[PDB]
Amino acid sequence: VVIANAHNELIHDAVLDYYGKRLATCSSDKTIKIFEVEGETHKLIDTLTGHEGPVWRVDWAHPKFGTILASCSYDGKVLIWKEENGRWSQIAVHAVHSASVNSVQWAPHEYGPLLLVASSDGKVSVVEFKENGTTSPIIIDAHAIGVNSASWAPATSRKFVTGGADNLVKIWKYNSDAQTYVLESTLEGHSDWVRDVAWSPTVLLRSYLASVSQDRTCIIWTQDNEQGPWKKTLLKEEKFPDVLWRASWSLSGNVLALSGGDNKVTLWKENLEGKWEPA
Image (cartoon, rainbow, N blue to C red; front, side, top):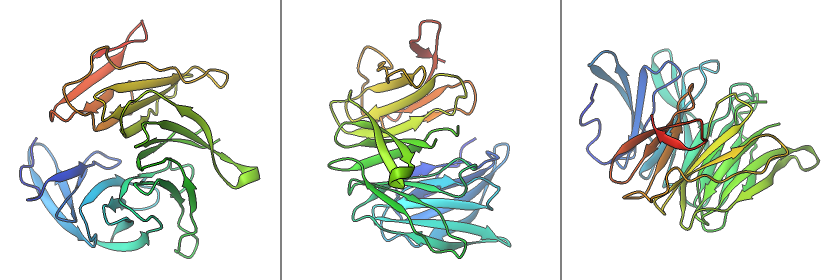
């Protein structure tokens, strides 16, 4: 199934929603597009407008809140969108960062309608939408140089991993006696900017993290339990041909989808040894 020419400017993100039927894209044209794919057909449904700069990413929210989509852009702001009564409209706007926002992600539906945001300004913001609408977020300084990604850990006590341009990967946990997310662990292992970080939703004892970097390597970080440390495990002994840009875990099977710069997508799974191989 292919939807050629969804945009005329280069596209940076395409995400299907909770039912994996409703597509959504974003690119330099500074717009988002909603699609409806079936067998091998497709129908545009709208074009979201507002961002003053190329749009970097989008994330669909859990259906239990409505039909929402979040986006962020080089313009250093985040826009939420809604499809009420049959038409999309900018409900809220989040802009507390002073540089390009590169990632945005809806927390687990159990936490409510929270949003995880990371920016080149080095900070990360956590945002909920009050009873009235406005937003009173959490802002933390999380990386030097710039933050490129941030992902939520599955639900139990709330944790999320960030990936900065300081080559570091970082786990965060919420604390009461601070009313903020505090730095739980710093994981060193990349020699160049970390482009993305994905926390696997696998519900097994062991937790899985996958970080991708400008150094042409993918690292799977794992933690057996609370007393265990985060163990480093290169996805493969040899570096890759080009820069790895994204990492995505399936919802089941704990299968990793790696997006390279040689515009190639490799798939991996774990084996008896604890080493990865092509799935």
